[PDB]
Amino acid sequence: ADLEDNWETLNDNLKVIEKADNAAQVKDALTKMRAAALDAQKATPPKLEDKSPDSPEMKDFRHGFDILVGQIDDALKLANEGKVKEAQAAAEQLKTTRNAYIQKYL
């Protein structure tokens, strides 16, 4: 599994969350999103294989996943309280972070 697989894992589990009926299902999918975000954060995106590991672009990339993981944790907290609809709405906003921070490097 590489960075592209991790990106598609995020997409598949966002669909799981969208279609979920209860908080347990949302928690499972958020778990897989968090795992894939951690794996992707350690990868070097194609457009940045050029750059040095501490370039402003690579810091952008890794920090986009720090923000994403923190937002996944916020959604997990909602799901852990039984707030299914709140957690699903939070998951929708994970696409805003994913698209704005990370997409420009794939």
Image: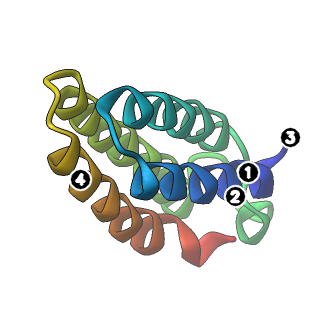
Q: Residues within 10 Å of mark 4 (few under 14, many from 20)?
A: some
Mark number displayed over residue 1: 3
Q: Residue at x 28, y 63 (%)?
A: 93
Q: Is residue 54 above or below residue 7?
A: above
Mark number displayed over residue 90: 4
Report the Cα–Cα distance between label 1 and label 4. Answer: 27 Å
Amino acid of disc 4: Ala
Q: Residue at x 21, y 36 (%)?
A: 74
Is 68 left or right of 3, judged from the image as shown?
A: left
- Location of the C terminus (image quadrant): bottom right
- Observer-nearest residue: 77 or 19? 19
| Mark 1 in CB contact with mark 2 (< 8 angstroms) | no
> What residue would you read off at disc 2?
8
How far from the left and from the top, in percent, is residue 83? 14, 36
Amino acid of disc 3: Ala
- Observer-nearest residue: 82 or 78? 82
Q: Is residue 35 above or below residue 44?
A: above
Q: Earlier in the sequence, mark 1 or mark 4?
A: 1
Q: Earlier in the sequence, mark 4 or mark 2?
A: 2
Which one is closest to the eye, mark 1 or mark 2? 2
Callout 1: SS:
loop
Q: Earlier in the sequence, mark 3 or mark 4?
A: 3
Q: Earlier in the sequence, mark 2 or mark 3?
A: 3
Is 36 left or right of 81, judged from the image as shown?
A: right
Q: Residue at x 19, y 50 (%)?
A: 85
Residue placed farthest to the top in the image? 80
Which one is closest to the eye, mark 1 or mark 3? 3
> What residue would you read off at disc 1?
44
Report the Cα–Cα distance between label 1 and label 3. Answer: 13 Å
Q: Earlier in the sequence, mark 1 or mark 3?
A: 3
Q: Residues within 10 Å of mark 3 (few under 14, many from 20)?
A: few
